[PDB]
Amino acid sequence: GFNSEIKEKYLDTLSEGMVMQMRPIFAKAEITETLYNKDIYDFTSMQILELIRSFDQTTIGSVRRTLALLSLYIDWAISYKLSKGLTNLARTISEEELYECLGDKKLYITYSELEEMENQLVNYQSKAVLRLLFEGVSGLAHSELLSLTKKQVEDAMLNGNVLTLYDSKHGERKLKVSSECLVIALNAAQETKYKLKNGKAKGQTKEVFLVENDYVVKTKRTSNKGDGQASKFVITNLITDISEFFKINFLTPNTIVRSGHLYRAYQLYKEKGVIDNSVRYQIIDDFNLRVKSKYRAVYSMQDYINEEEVNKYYAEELGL
């Protein structure tokens, strides 16, 4: 592409599979290279992030793989003193910064993405809102999530992981969830402090107090609301703080819930080869969704529960 001779020299050293991986990267990089009028090996770290973002990739995994290949090319270029500077600025990049490169095609998250994010989050309030929304504990006005108590979590733990949720408008509803979900919620329901900027605060105050109660989602004491149930704005703010840590713009209660549905669809698509209305029926049943007419909802789901989307996000898991 840009710097044809050098590129092809490096491609000669590769193993064809690697060459098939690199040809598209160099192709899509040509234009950023010609704009900056330099090769990738002289790019700065932020310029490398801008490049990878310009690839518009939908998973943190594909982003990690892309960065790795670029780092290999850069090591190569350093060894031959082609690079102006002699350090691999692609190696100085941190785990959160990669989420900047996730492009804007992305709307939904994969289960592996969820676990990685959770791992990077110091507060159990954050982990909990993410996980519980993923597994379907959202209600109308998030009533099922905001009324959730430690006792409900414990009972579920002693009940084959079946939560009895309370939506204020529609009433009671049962939901089987994972043990990870329940342990995370158990910790969240006992958390007394919340670390600002995901534990990377610069100023004098690093944490703030939460209210004293038995609810999983807890208001902050300063907010002047009661020591009882939290409002929907607490969930909005928790997700905002997460999005700011990872510098991403697609997270919404809706998209998280639907990511859960999509992951279930991926599993069933592996098991049974194709997604159809039986798969969608099964999803309605597993997440025990409130529907007036089953069939109306089955076809209403086709917009996001389909093969195009499952493949789009779960390709590598599919081995495609």
Image (cartoon, rainbow, N blue to C red):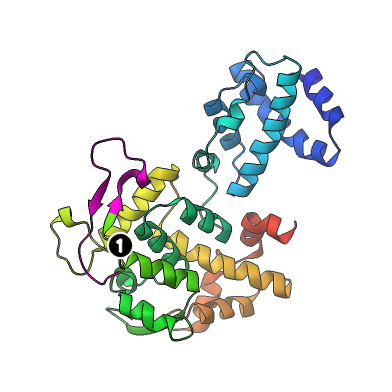
Is residue 219 found left or right of 163 in the rendered image? left
Image quadrant where one finds the C terminus: bottom right
Give the structural element (helix, strand or loop) at label 1. Answer: loop
Q: Residue at x 81, y 18 (%)?
A: 5
Residue 238, can we see it? yes
Please tell me whether residue 22 is drawn above or below residue 242 in the rendered image.
above
Q: Residue at x 65, y 59 (%)?
A: 308
Is residue 109 found left or right of 125 in the rendered image? right
Residue 75 at x, y percent in the picture: 71, 26
Image quadrant where one finds the N terminus: top right
Residue 258 at x, y percent in the picture: 49, 65
| Magenta-highlighted residues | 194-215
Quarter of the image where one finds residue 283: bottom right
Quarter of the image where one finds residue 225: bottom left
Closer to the camera in the image, 251 or 120: 120
Closer to the camera in the image, 96 or 109: 96
Q: Which kind of residue does numbered mark 1 sit on?
A: Glu
Closer to the camera in the image, 262 or 190: 190
Magenta stretch contains residue 211: yes
Query: How would you rate the neighbour count of disc 1 (Cα within 10 Å): few for under 14, some for 14-19, many for 20 or more?
Result: many
Magenta stretch contains residue 64: no
Residue 42 at x, y percent in the picture: 63, 19
Please tell me whether residue 265 is drawn above or below residue 225 in the rendered image.
below
Quarter of the image where one finds residue 12: top right
Please tell me whether residue 268 is drawn above or below residue 196 in the rendered image.
below
Q: Residue at x 40, y 47 (%)?
A: 243
Q: Residue at x 86, y 38 (%)?
A: 16
Is residue 192 found left or right of 302 in the rendered image? left
Please tell me whether residue 19 is drawn above or below residue 160 in the rendered image.
above
Residue 194 at x, y percent in the picture: 29, 53
Give the residue pinned by disc 1: 191
Residue 1, can we see it? no
